[PDB]
Image (tube, coloured by chain):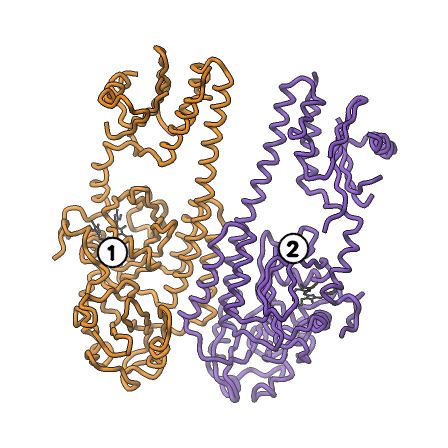
Chain colours: A orange, B purple
């Protein structure tokens, strides 16, 4: 069973069920049917039964021809074919994962997207990514152009803070709906297994939210005695908790393109529709390549950005060092608000201490803290939240230095699952918390301390 | 006719003939046939006659249906369909340019490429474009990878320098073949239209270089009294001159991917094969969009590069300026050999004259150069090449300043159309030319002069 307590540990990769807008058949390396969704018969007029092998006369030669090239293939398999089965024309998408072949039958409802038309989609959307040299212009723009394309009546962009928390930094919607810019959720709104997934799968599609799931039997793969891993499965089934959530938002359909930097989910575009919605495989696949592109483009942008700040910052220290080391008045050099140490780490208030002379730039909380490290008289460095009147406190020893950050920063069934609700349970974790001390800010205070360890007079 | 005097100005966009591995039907806005290749009967049943409209029984319904989307659609039309005609299976690729609709029927010879397969060709190659930061490594890799994908007996990357000239900076070949790395051809090897075209069309295909071509009648479009513009045409026929050339190179098939920055062809991938060779439209199409991606990547990658050198460059100047503006005897401040002038623009030797004092870094020539700006006694700047003992010469007045660059840089029917015969024709353009003075160098020597125009004592 799934509650607000079993939220973060839910194995959403191995649900043993799929959404109903298609059907699943799984097979072992030799083509034998190991399991299938319970709707096959309804959808397709086969009754795939374990031990069976599919035959032209239920699945068409186009499928088997396909699957064969999968069975006699060497690497990770992925492919698909647009066959017509008895009742309907189909998008049948296969792929092998672990040691299992999945055949997912998703219902095609269109004409054929020319191998060309497909391209101008991809190219039309990539085009947006390459106009801009600013990371936020980028998101703002593509966020628009995606809507013009899909028709999804809400499409947003999310950025993910280092704490894996989440913020809505771009949006385009149908006016009727409430706006979302600036909204913040917790890391806890997207579990490590969903996040892990979104990293693996560029694109996730929820066809209908209140869908009533369709199960695969056996729920467990006899060959392996483990359940079936449906990551990389298209009709894989969505966690109920997240289904409740979307409904509490008044949403019926979904889709998300991923953005990935490092090996991490840097953020994602999320598509919402007030009614059910289904983007075809082929289109999704224009977006899959979009995502690859987008992520790259965003990665090099961001490495350049921080590379820069990182430079502007270190050039500062080094400047400050020659200035102090080459003057005799260090108190006057070290505390000039422009040659100010405050210039070095991003803070609200700072402090130079050496001898019996102090200066509170931007003094009392300092009587206490030099009293805290009294039980630690061999520390040359100090750092903390959530703590007088300022919570951020970083302290380096040479004679001391201090940097501060105060933190003025900024129906249904379950307790938390809503927009303004996840932000209500976001806040209570962040009032103890000043803007956390960047991996860069410990390196700055550190280099600086050492740097002044140098001055002999 | 086409000779070496006449190759500069050739209209390769309007030949009035295509290549034989396909067929072409041009049609006006109401779909009436205005022209057709001469092999239309040879390749297909019909005799497409100006005036005629296509009928299902000539061309299939898939094409007629396609063309219909085109005739009623509004903007640039681009599209294809895979239809069986009488004799063969085809890739009918169509598009509209100016006010004409082209229907190219290129011979399909494979099984259908799935949308998925189409997608990882794309992503496989894109993936190669986003591992590296160095502009050079990037090229070096995709060069390799394209060979692993097409099989082209040769794969290469060209780079073009601001003087519209060309260098080969990446290779992957069948070893039996001479290696081209480090070769250099003039701008004259790719005429303005070639180049301008290579910018519009990302991709070009040549299947048999000794192909005896296929005309289209009427050579001239009644509606417009001007020839048909095959700019965007796939089967567009290639200049004879470039053919005579490739065969002198012993090459029967060719394929080019564009890399574009600014509105400018920054470089390209030329693929060569020593027997005839055709890469299917759908596959072409994946490279077409790779051309988009690679082009953007390199644009940012390169703009960071130049931006840096552009920053270190100006940083130096401004460094030197505060060091003299704030210092006392300038002949020596301008002249710690490291705070030196030569350390501000790329040269081989430089010179600082003022008063009656000279110092030849890296004096006599000084009395002669001031004697050649005697007939221009009010020149504060001077710049030249091809010229004493140096041909690159740039001069600034405040007392003067000079920077130097010497020049030790580095069958058929017509003479020059050969690899080493183009490189031989190249040397003449460069034997009396030093590395030209960049837009940047004229800005440095300028800002500097201005900077030293501030000094009073
Ligand atoms: C304003 C909107 C808003 C949302 C949507 C939010 C949480 C949130 N949960 C998400 C996915 C998800 N969230 C969950 C599970 C959970 N979901 C939970 O809220 C909790 C507490 C759990 C687990 C403890 C799952 C399983 C997914 C992805 C499911 C899938 O697509 O497979 C997503 C990503 C997909 C999307 O954008 O639609 C968000 C933004 N916080 C917000 O402020
Ligand atoms: C070692 C190899 C080498 C080459 C390939 C070269 C010139 C050269 N000519 C090119 C295209 C071309 N060159 C021409 C025409 C000319 N070509 C000429 O050399 C001249 C003198 C003219 C006309 C005055 C045309 C028309 C094309 C492109 C044709 C097309 O693809 O439509 C290309 C691009 C396509 C390719 O690389 O195959 C090159 C590199 N110089 C060299 O040293």
Q: Which mark is residue A242?
A: none
Q: Nearer the viewer, residue B454 or A32?
A: A32
Give the percent coordinates (x, y) of residue B201.
59, 64
Q: Residue furthest left?
A: A1
Q: Share a chain, discs 1 and 2?
A: no
Secondary structure at badge 2 equals strand
| Residue underneath mark 1 | A251
Alpha-carbon span between mark 1 and mark 2: 53 Å
- Residue A83: quarter of image: bottom left
| Residue underneath mark 2 | B160
Give the percent coordinates (x, y) of residue B442.
70, 38
How many marks the image carries: the answer is 2
Q: Chain of mark 2?
A: B
Q: Is residue B189 left or right of residue B67?
A: right
Q: Is residue B322 left or right of residue B377?
A: left
Could you tell me which residue is drawn at 85 percent across and 30 percent down? B367
- Residue B99: quarter of image: bottom right
Quarter of the rendering occupied by the C terminus of chain B:
top right
Secondary structure at badge 1 equals loop
Q: Mark 1 vs ligand 1: CB under 8 Å?
A: yes
Could you tell me which residue is drawn at 47 percent across and 64 percent down? A120
Eyeballing the image, is B103 above or below B166? below
Crowd class of label 2 (few under 14; some 14 to 19; many from 20; radius 10 Å): some
Could you tell me which residue is drawn at 32 percent across and 83 percent down? A60
Give the percent coordinates (x, y) of residue B81.
47, 76
Residue B226 in sight here: no
Give the percent coordinates (x, y) of residue A132.
48, 48
Q: Mark 2 vs ligand 2: CB under 8 Å?
A: no
Q: Is the residue under label 2 in contact with that under label 1 (CB below 8 Å)? A: no
Q: Chain of mark 1?
A: A
């Amino acid at each position: 069973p799934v509650t607000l307590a079993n939220c973060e540990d839910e194995p959403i990769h191995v649900p043993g069920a799929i959404q109903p807008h298609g059907a699943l058949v799984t097979l072992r390396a030799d083509g034998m049917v190991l399991a299938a969704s319970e709707n096959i018969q309804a959808l397709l007029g086969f009754v795939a039964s374990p031990g069976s092998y599919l035959t032209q006369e239920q699945v068409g030669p186009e499928v088997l021809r396909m699957l064969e090239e999968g069975l006699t293939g060497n690497g990770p398999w992925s492919n698909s074919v647009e066959t017509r089965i008895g009742e309907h024309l189909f998008d049948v998408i296969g792929h092998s994962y672990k040691e299992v072949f999945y055949l997912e039958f998703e219902i095609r409802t269109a004409d054929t997207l020319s191998i060309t038309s497909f391209t101008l989609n991809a190219q039309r959307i990539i085009a947006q990514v390459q106009l801009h040299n600013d990371t936020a212009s980028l998101l703002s723009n593509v966020t628009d152009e995606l809507r013009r394309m899909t028709g999804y009546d809400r499409v947003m962009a999310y950025r993910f803070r280092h704490d894996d928390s989440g913020e809505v930094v771009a949006e385009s919607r149908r006016e009727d709906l409430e706006s979302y810019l600036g909204l913040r959720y917790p890391a806890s709104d997207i579990p490590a297994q969903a996040r892990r997934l979104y990293i693996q799968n560029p694109i996730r599609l929820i066809a209908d939210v209140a869908y009533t799931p369709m199960r695969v039997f056996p729920a467990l793969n006899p060959e392996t005695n483990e359940s079936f891993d449906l990551s990389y499965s298209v009709l894989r089934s969505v966690s109920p908790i997240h289904c409740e959530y979307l409904t509490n938002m008044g949403v019926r359909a979904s889709m998300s393109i991923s953005i990935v930097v490092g090996g991490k989910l840097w953020g994602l575009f999320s598509c919402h529709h007030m009614s059910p919605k289904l983007i075809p495989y082929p289109v999704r696949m224009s977006f899959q390549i979009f995502s690859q592109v987008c992520s790259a483009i965003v990665e090099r942008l961001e490495q350049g950005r921080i590379a820069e700040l990182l430079r502007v910052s270190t050039e500062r220290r080094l400047a400050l060092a020659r200035r102090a080391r080459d003057a005799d008045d260090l108190f006057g050099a070290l505390a000039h608000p422009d040659d100010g140490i405050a210039a070095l780490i991003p803070c609200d208030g700072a402090l130079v201490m050496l001898g019996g002379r102090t200066l509170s730039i931007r003094e009392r909380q300092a009587g206490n803290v030099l009293q805290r490290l009294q039980r630690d008289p061999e520390r040359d460095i100090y750092h903390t939240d959530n703590w007088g009147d300022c919570c951020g406190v970083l302290a380096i020893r040479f004679g001391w230095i201090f940097w501060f950050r105060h933190e003025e920063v900024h129906g249904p069934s379950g307790p938390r699952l809503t927009p303004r609700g996840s932000f209500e349970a976001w806040e209570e974790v962040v009032r103890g918390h000043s803007t956390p001390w960047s991996e860069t800010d410990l390196a700055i205070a550190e280099k600086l301390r050492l740097d002044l360890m140098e001055l002999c007079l």
